[PDB]
Image (cartoon, rainbow over all chains, first blue to last red; front, top):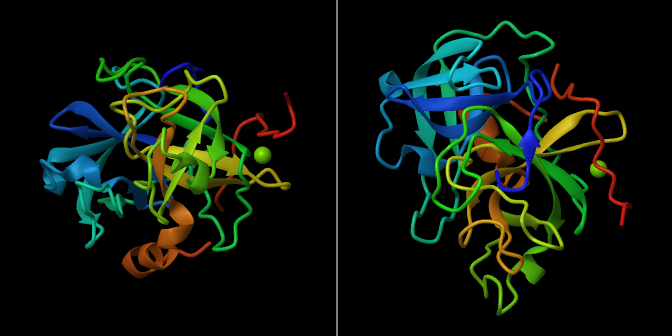
Length: 234
Length: 15
Ligand SMILES: [Mg+2]
């Protein structure tokens, strides 16, 4: 995360680190006690569940809980070159016992109100500058949703933002997801203070450039896929 | 069952 702050322990109870061969690789979000929602890109080199561990806690150096992974599911139409359908599910070996500090985020309704300009939080252990090192403690950034149409301006992504994607950033630039944040959540809460995952960190042109907002998988576009793969509604 | 989160708000109206 560029332009963010360190998150407090317990702030983001759904956030997990997905570790490949004992190093942080991707973020993800608990969507129930046995399933994590993340990005397909996370698994481009390794989709062996036995080589992945999910952790909870704000530190990837000293995690609070380590969780074995049973299966990794990638969207069947993930296309890496265009980033289309960048979404994946991780099934845990054991059901997590939920607490205040570890529990699930809600899935959005198909009609979830996600207006252009609306503020949202993005979280992860990614770099603070493009292609830089990961950070050991979870960071958070507050961004605004940027409509696909605006995101597709000629000086921005010029048509590369597709309907199952969404964009987010801030008016001045400098707040964004970055390398190592892939798979982590973009979240908004409703009037009852229930938090929903509206986006999954996916890609962007470098990080934090004002004309190049971060690009996310649009969760509403995949609700049927998630329900089919897991049974979960929402 | 899902969605309990932090003492933070995403207000859209601040300038
Ligand atoms: Mg809000």
